[PDB]
Image (cartoon, coloured by chain):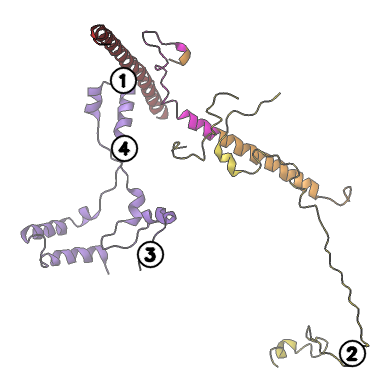
Chain colours: A purple, B orange, C yellow, D red
Amino acid sequence: AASTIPISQWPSLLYAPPSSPANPAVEALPEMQFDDLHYPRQMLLCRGAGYSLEQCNRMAQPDARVTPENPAEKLLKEEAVAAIACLSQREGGKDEQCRYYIERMYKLANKE
Amino acid sequence: RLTFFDTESVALQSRLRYAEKQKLFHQELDRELAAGHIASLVAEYDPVATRLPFQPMQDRYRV
Amino acid sequence: PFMWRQRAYCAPVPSAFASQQGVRKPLLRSNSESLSVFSQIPDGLLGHTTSVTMGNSDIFFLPKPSNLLKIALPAFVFMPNLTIFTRAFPFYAHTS
Amino acid sequence: NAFSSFDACRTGLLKQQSAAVENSLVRQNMADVRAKALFERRAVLLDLVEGK
């Protein structure tokens, strides 16, 4: 059923992957970013402005141009906190002990 | 025929001039890319290695 | 213009790294010129090669000896008769 | 707004070039001094060497 993906189809595989029990956001895969040039560029700009290494290191800040945050963390806050409480109390939800909260979250997120 | 019954010559001349423009564009573009490829080596170029031991560096090699 | 050591097709030829050679030939050339036909070769006789024509060779001759034959032969019908029942032809053409 | 970033990156590149030249000169000179000292050490050890 799962047939081989040739090498020519890998660029399409990266941005339209097959279905899994744990899929990513295919619509947001073009939005995942992490700049390895952020701090070097910052340092170059500051040293061109005229600062010393200590001043540059004090002014350095981490990149804001990274992958956006999951909106579920702000929308389903209380539900997620309750689920985490249930997991911490019931040993990770063994034998279906956090099914209540997990099903409420799933329904809220999916809507049939 | 050529005096009264031909448009192919004119059409082909126009198309060949178009082809010439296209050819020279592609030529210049390829040349530009190769020049950029060579320009990528200026970072590797080290003019201090031309210095001889216990000798001064020459401005000939773009200090 | 981004990955020079990994994109060799867009790179200069090894004669360009050599620093030694009216009008001279150009010093810098790419391998991407290999993707063009008339880069190095000339465009001479470009549009005049489809005009060199040659005629066919078939001869339509066959003796027709009917003295050998004394019987008729079958013949195909090639098209429908429109000189008769012209008005009804779209209406009866599908029958048999 | 664009000229500011351009001038900054520009001066950064210039400083990089200057620092690279200086550091390469220093490294070269250190290596040459070390090599000379090794050569003299070899010379004295060849004056001390023994055999035929």
Looking at the rendered structure, whether the residues under marks 4 and 3 are on a common chain is answered as: yes
Q: Quadrant of the C terminus of chain A?
A: bottom left
Residue C69's disc is: 2
Residue occupied by mark 3: A3
Q: Amino acid at mark 1?
A: Gly
Q: Is residue B24 left or right of residue D8?
A: right
How far apart marks 1 and 2 lie (CA) works out to: 113 Å
Q: Is residue D49 above or below residue A11?
A: above
| Point 92% across, 86% down: residue | C66
Q: Work out whether mark 1 precedes mark 3 in sequence or the reverse, and give the earlier one.
A: 3
In front of the other: label 2 or label 4? Answer: 2
Query: In which image quadrant can residue A27 be found?
Result: bottom left
Q: Is residue A82 above or below residue C9?
A: below
Q: Amino acid at mark 4?
A: Asp
| Point 64% across, 44% down: residue | C37
Residue occupied by mark 4: A36
Q: Is residue C13 magenta?
A: no
Q: Position of residue A58 (x, y in %)?
A: 21, 27
In front of the other: label 1 or label 4? Answer: 4
Looking at the rendered structure, whether the residues under marks 1 and 3 are on a common chain is answered as: yes
Q: Is residue A80 above or below residue B2?
A: below
In front of the other: label 1 or label 2? Answer: 2
Looking at the rendering, the stretch of residues picked out in magenta corresponds to B32-59
